[PDB]
Amino acid sequence: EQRDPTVHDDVLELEMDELNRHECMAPLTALVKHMHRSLGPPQGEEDSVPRDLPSWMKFLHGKLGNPIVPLNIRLFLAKLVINTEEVFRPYAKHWLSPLLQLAASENNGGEGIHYMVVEIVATILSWTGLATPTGVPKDEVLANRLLNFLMKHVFHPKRAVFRHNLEIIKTLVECWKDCLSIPYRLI
DNA sequence: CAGCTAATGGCCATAATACCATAATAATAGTTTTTA
């Protein structure tokens, strides 16, 4: 690396067909699917690392540039099976994801902002008490900025195009808060 | 007668009238929205 699937934003600056046209996932999918049937209901992990470093899920990192994006794009349907806290740090990857990166991708396609955050957070609710992590330990700066941008954007595009689009977010908004970072006076 | 009347020739102000023409509001519908 880099390799072509690891050369990313060189083109394709909106998010639509990177899931459709990357032509990479589907093997990666059943890949981590079946070998995750090996590592799976056989054993779960409240931890990030033990499912990665021995896994090829370590190969997945998703930090620092385009090195971020596709890997965690990889995480997309990955976490479908993955959870629990096994994606613990990858979670931190996720709230990390939108910040200057989806920002770097900007609107990233009309439905893009969704396309990221949809399960960026919608995984946050993939658990209850495991969101005690989502709030407290490493979210430290994370969700604060996160929200800031998120909100910041999502205000208009409804204004730009049409309505309950945001509301889709307004949900997420709702979904957030049992304590969190309060960019709210700022709201 | 006396002087031609004197109501004849004319008719301007009016008030009335009209058309005729709006806000003070209060409606229509309206084209978008997805849903189906």
Image: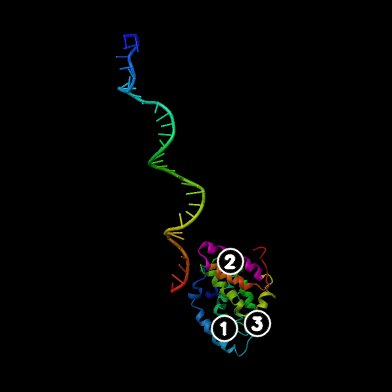
**Three-letter code, disc 2:** Ala
The answer, for residue A34, to whether it is visible in the render is yes
Q: Nearer the viewer, residue A80 or B26?
A: B26
Which residue has dot 1 on it? A81
The answer, for residue A1, to whether it is visible in the render is no
Q: Residues within 10 Å of mark 3 (few under 14, many from 20)?
A: some
Label 1 residue SS: helix
Which label number is shown at residue A103?
2
State yes or no: residue A104 in magenta: no
- Residue B36 drawn at (x, y percent): 43, 74
- Residue depicted at 55% across the width and 69% down the height: A167
Chain identifier of the residue bearing label 1 in the image = A
Which residue has dot 3 on it? A49
Residues rendered magenta in the picture:
A142-164
Is A149 situated above or below B12?
below
**Three-letter code, disc 3:** Val
- Residue A186 drawn at (x, y percent): 66, 63
Label 3 residue SS: helix
Label 2 residue SS: helix
Q: Earlier in the sequence, mark 1 or mark 3?
A: 3
- Residue A124 drawn at (x, y percent): 62, 76
